[PDB]
Image (cartoon, one colour):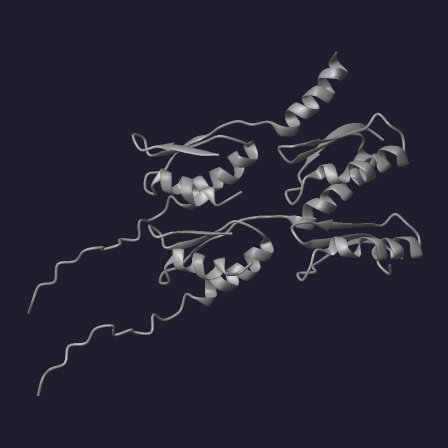
Length: 51
Length: 137
Length: 86
């Protein structure tokens, strides 16, 4: 249940494509999350290590 | 609970992108904050070191999210401008032939993979023997 | 006025911009220029052979880094040789 940020890549297509469904897992459980999609094409999450 | 300003970078994309969620942490607790996003691409917070710390953590969470450094590595052999061209197909790059050294512009992922390609085409020149001198019998 | 100058100076120090002038004894400035130009500003003089900079004290940190990076040996190109026929 720790809160950490994870930075991981999707090389294939811009990850803005996942904003609604990922905020579904930001909705599915508790917030304090971020998921920020860098136009440099890497990936940010922050929050509970599980979610 | 001290009030200080913190100036930190997000190199990767314009930090105006974080204005609503950062003002969420300017809303989440007491105000007296600022978070001002300089089009020169650095970052300003002002306020309580805690909430300025959390603000710098989302902020630095878009910093570390897309950081960008550079490398300078020798190409003793293969023409840099060639190394350039032959990576150009890949979808940036410099070198010097005073030194004969690859320079890079971009990611520490570009630093991982392009130290890989620093190494990849360094090897033997394979003795082209472009010319020979045949001694007529 | 002090608090106003503190938000104000908080956008001053937020994006300050100075300049540097550093010798390039060796590598052609205009080349140093070109080869940084790919990076996404720059001057020099070949009276002095010295990098000049226009921009950040971050540009001052990293471009004193590149002041230093391509200063080194010329690596004795030996572009030409004179072979004594046996």
